[PDB]
Each structure stands twice: as C-alpha cells, then as structure tokens.
Amino acid sequence: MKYIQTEQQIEVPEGVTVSIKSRIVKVVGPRGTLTKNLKHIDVTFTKVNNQLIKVAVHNGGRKHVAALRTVKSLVDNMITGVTKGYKYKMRYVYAHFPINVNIVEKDGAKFIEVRNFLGDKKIRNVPVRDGVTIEFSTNVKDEIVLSGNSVEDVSQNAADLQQICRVRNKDIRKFLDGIYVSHKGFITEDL
Amino acid sequence: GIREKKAEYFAKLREYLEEYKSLFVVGVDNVSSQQMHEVRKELRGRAVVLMGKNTMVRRAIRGFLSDLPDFEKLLPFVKGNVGFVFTNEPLTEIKNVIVSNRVAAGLTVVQVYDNGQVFPXXXXXXXXXXXXXXXXXXXXXXX
RNA sequence: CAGUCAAGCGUUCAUAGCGACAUUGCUUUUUGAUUCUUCGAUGUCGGCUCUUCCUAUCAUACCGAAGCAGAAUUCGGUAAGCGUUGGAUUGUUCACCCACUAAUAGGGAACGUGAGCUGGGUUUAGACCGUCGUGAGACAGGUUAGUUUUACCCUACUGAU
RNA sequence: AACUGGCGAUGCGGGAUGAACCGAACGUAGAGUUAAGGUGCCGGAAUACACGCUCAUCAGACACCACAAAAGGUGUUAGUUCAUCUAGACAGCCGGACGGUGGCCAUGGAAGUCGGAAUCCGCUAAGGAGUGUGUAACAACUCACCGGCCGAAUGAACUAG
RNA sequence: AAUACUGCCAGCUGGGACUGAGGACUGCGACGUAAGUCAAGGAUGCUGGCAUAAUGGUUAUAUGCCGCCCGUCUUGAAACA
C-alpha cells in the first residue's frame, strides 16, 4: 500500500571503502574488492559518514519491500565475502564401491576424478569454480573444503556439485549415496 | 482477537505489580516444562514463576506503567529470557530460587560497613576535630 | 473423454493404488430432430494406390513420484524428433486367427483419394429354389450371370528455354 | 400459438462482414448543423486532459456480434468480522522443565512416557499421575510453563477487484 | 469587502462564409420643423487585363475514393440455382 519512504540502513565498518558511482558501487574490503551493477534498483544510495549507507526509494511498494528487505541480506552477504569470505566443507557417500575422489588437473581447470562410482567404468570429473578455493579436507574421509566470497560462489558450487551425484536407475529412495554437504564456514574462520 | 487475552492475561499480569512490589528477573530460556511442571509440585511454599513472550508482551510491558510505574522495568529485561514473578520478599530472595532447581533445560547510610564495625555515618566522616583534636587529649592527660 | 467430491476399499492407510453417492465440462472420428443446396443430376461400396494433417503419444529421447532390494513395477512431466510387420478364412468395411517387432497410438483431408485403378458384393432385363399372393405379382429369403468415355483448354504443378 | 416492429415492397449514415440489428428513410441543388457512430496508423477527428486496477511462460481490446464451467490459486488489490492485540506476545534466538510418584499399577518390563486403571497434594518464574522421545524400565533428552531480547503484530472467518 | 453562480441589456468593438433571389411606382416604415434622409415589400458604387480556345466542353491519358454478369424462382441468388 505504498509505504511512503523505503530504505535499507546498513552500518559500514572501517576496513572497507566503497564508491557509489550514482548507483554503481566500488566495494573494497580487507580481503579484497567487490562491485555490483545496482542500476536495477533505482534508489538514492546514502553514505552518512563511513558507518552507514541507506538506499532510498521515495514511496516504495509491497513486493518492492519483499525484495527490498533482502537487498540488505545480500548486501551483508557481500560484506562477509569482501571482508571475511565463506568456507564450506562437503561430503561424499558410497557404501560398497570405494569412489576415488581427486582434483585431477586439466590445465588448472581442476577436475575431480570420481572413480568406482557404484561400479561404473565411467568416470566423473568435476572442474573447480574458481574464486571459491578448495582444499581436501584432510584427516576426514568423504569431506572437502571450499572457500569463496559469495554464498553462491560456494553454495552454487555446492549446489551443482551437489547435482553431480544425482543418482538414478535404482530404487533410490532406498539406494542412498553421493556428494552431500557437511559444513559451511569462513575463509578467515572465526570471521 | 489477542488483545482481550492481553486484557485478561494482563488483567491478572498487569494486576499484581503493586500487589507484589519486588523484582526477580529469571533467566529461563528453552524451558524444560517437564521439570518446570514438577517445580509446581514443589511450589507449595511461596510463589510461582509467571513468564511472557516479552516482545508480544512488549506493548504490554509498555502497558506496565500503571501501578508503580517502576513495573515497566521488564522491557529493560526483554532480551535475555525473561518474564514475571509475584511475591512480597523484597530484593533477592526468589531469583536465587527459580533459576537453580528443576529449571528450564531509595535507601540512605546510617551504617557504614567497614570490617564488621558499627558506624553512625558520622564517625569515619567526622569533622576531623572530634578525634584529630583528641590526639592531644591523653597527651594533655599524659602531661 | 475430462474433471469436482468422497462413503469407503486398499493389513493398517481415503488418496501407493483405488473408489459409494453426487457434481462440472469436452468431442465429433455415433446415433436421434433438421430440410437451407441438388430432381434443365457435383461418378454413392469395398479394396488398391499415394500424400499430408492433428493429438487426446504405441515405441523411441529426457525427467519426476509409489504400498518402486536387484530384477521386475505403477503414476506423472517434457514430449508428434523418428518409427510403429507378414500370411489362413471372409467382396468385404468389419471380424477372427497364425506368426514378428523397440512398438505393432488414435482420428482429419466433400465420411482425402474411379478425365487414378479394379469392380468381388451391391442393383435392369435372363435363370433356379424356399416362403406369400387367385392373379397380375411380392419376398433387407437364398442362389446364377449379366456393356467403367474424354485434357490438344484454364488453373495447379514440373522440367525447359 | 396471442402483442409490437422490419424485410418482402426500401435506399442512405454505425456494427471489418452481415434481409429483418443502431441512426435516419428517398425531388434537383447549394450555404450553415448533427444523429448512429466514433478521434494511436490505415483513420476523418485529440498518443486531449483527470482518478484508479492490472503485467497476463495462455492479459485485454465488448449491443448487434460471432461464447466456458464446477472446482480452485499465501497471485494481486482493498476492505469486513471475531479472538490474542504494544500489557511485547509474535517472529527469531538464549535453559530446565518436578519432590511426594514407578499414583493404583495391569508389573518378567512400564521409572512420566507397552498396557489397564483413577488423574492427586503441592511446587514455582517452571514441572504434566507426567509432553513425547529415549523406553529391559529407563536414565536422560524433551515439550507445555516459566525465565533473556524486539517494538508489533498474532490467530480465525472472510469479502470481492 | 471580494468571488462562484445564474439571468438581463431592445450595452460596445474583430473575423469568416453565403446571397442580391426581385425589378417604373405604390406599401410598410422610421429619421429630420420642414426640406430632406433612411438600411422601409431582396444590390448598389470604384479597377485592371484578355478580347482569345482566354474561359469552358470534349476525347484520350493519368491521378484519390467506391464499384459480385444478366434473366429468373423463392421468404432467401453474385451464388455450388
């Protein structure tokens, strides 16, 4: 019902410097940098004094709020990336057939040997979405460590990497294996 | 309608503020209502813990200025897990009771208390001539 | 043909799989009413041939869900991309076997298709039986044989210059 | 079949199209004026102005006149009513949640939680003859409740664009 | 006090288009003492050019808009009558 002034009011810390080119932000954090095309929101962006920035919509709408709240959510997600950065850990499952897992290299493409995929002579190979940066989770079977700066850097990688082992052909509501997830974390852990 | 459960539940809860003029903020989150039911099987001594969802009770405790306007003070205790207690024991005699067992799972100075002594608040803070001039007292009675 | 609804079934459990009583729509590829056109008449059976359409999809492609150990299922989505047989009898249309496939989906094209084919049935006059009639005759009784022209014109189309 | 009105027998202006529909009927003409009917382009004549709805992986764009329902849909919009309703609940998160009590126990187990049986006194800010789980029983976890925040929303019936 | 609103004036000034139909005279009128005026039964004053295919008809061409064979029956024909 057209609430008369809608806005998101986000505290700015001091390890970060941005620059909003009239809608277009130049994000800089203690980890690195981000930007975004924000010429799809039509706000007045609002520095106060390096400790909060609002957006500004004169008389925002209902579904405009239904996206405009989580505007702040996804902004703060970008803050956690540009400062701190996510670091998940996933899972593997087999029961009978020991799946070899390897980040095999194709020219830095960083595929993944998936071998003995339930007796398959076919091999899977998964390239690495770069930016999100992965080590093997050592000392733990069936885990691995991703570390990026978007929640879809690491959860889109974990999403379609999760979609690697969409297993068919059996009574799979009984037959349960595959790439799963364990954990979600942070590049600087404890940040 | 929920506001007449706030007129009933805060008829009886906004009621006893000046009936029972003591404060006991009990920190019972995540409440073992098994054990805290058996609390009531034990509660035939003095009182019963009487809590509230204090953001739903936010405008209710905003409604607690009524009898001793000091009873709005459970909005200064809304974050943390918090609610209400009714008894006539004056300062800290029920907050020591509810939190321990079977649980979730002004005033002036006429007595300065220095080393078990009895000051009238006029001995230590004297005129420094009611004793400092009495340093030559038994010096004078001496000589 | 498709819903809505559920009494219940389905060990139990309405909804895996179903579904009592009820209810809403859809189709002309079925039958009723109907007489606008045709009696100075537009080749009506069946088959052959040959092409296209449609989807409400048989198979083939991808998927999803179950009262889906494997194996073997059900139900659904995307789905018309491509495919979806040979002979005995019967003019047959139809029908039924016998055999094969991944599978042997379903309809339209003036009930697609005779200056495209045949003419087996159908239907002159000839002839026979069974029934009915005095009879002239009648029999969706049975039976038998008994005359398929023409584009060098236009359009269409395809080669050609 | 009983009333009025047209075609027939009758033209002109609107419905892209229209026997019987919207205006209006007929001398030759001419100057001013309109119906019906309209003024993005064709298109004559305003992409004139004012307040709102809507965004449609199947809008919509109409007497004549040339068409969907039952059933729905946290889609939208707005309200209507009821009960919590700022006295803060709610959301979100921060802990236990009974002593008598395994009530009587049916007790090979049943300790709150297989199962019959009555449902206790209390206790609180909470504790239930137990809220389940965990259960040889259980322990214990757990949940009501009550204990920390927030400032306002909660729950139900709707109602129709 | 203003202002809306409405009605009245037989108040005052721009532009368009269309017309002169009629032919002595009457009449109706008004206006001026009269004379005389007038707008009172429909129009009367000042130019310039051509003096011809000038204008105009005609045919043919070309353009903007409209345009189902006659004759026939039926209530219904452009009719696949």
Image: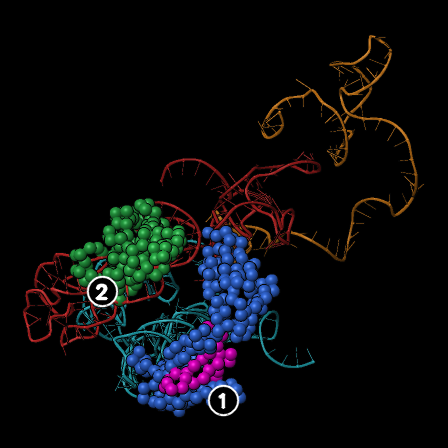
Chain colours: A blue, B green, C cyan, D red, E orange
Membership of A156 in magenta stretch:
no
Q: Position of residue E54 (x, y in %)?
A: 86, 45
What is the number of the mark on residue B101? 2
Q: Quadrant of the C terminus of chain B?
A: bottom left
Residue drawn at the location 53% of the way across and 88% of the way down: A107
| Along the line of sight, the residue nearer the viewer: B65 or A170 | B65
Kindly give the residue lying farthest to the bottom in the view shown: A121
Residue stretch in magenta: A126-151
Crowding near pointer 1: few (<14 within 10 Å), some, many (20+)? some
Report the number of discs. Answer: 2
Q: Which residue is mark 1?
A: A105
Kindly give the residue lying farthest to the front in the view shown: B143
Callout 1 amino acid: Glu
Q: Relative to B32, does residue D24 appear above or below in the rendering?
A: above
| Along the line of sight, the residue nearer the viewer: B43 or C147 | B43
Q: Relative to C125, does residue B8 appear above or below in the rendering?
A: above
Callout 2 amino acid: Asn
Residue drawn at the location 59% of the way across and 66% of the way down: A19
Mark 2–mark 1 distance (CA, rounded to whole Å): 61 Å
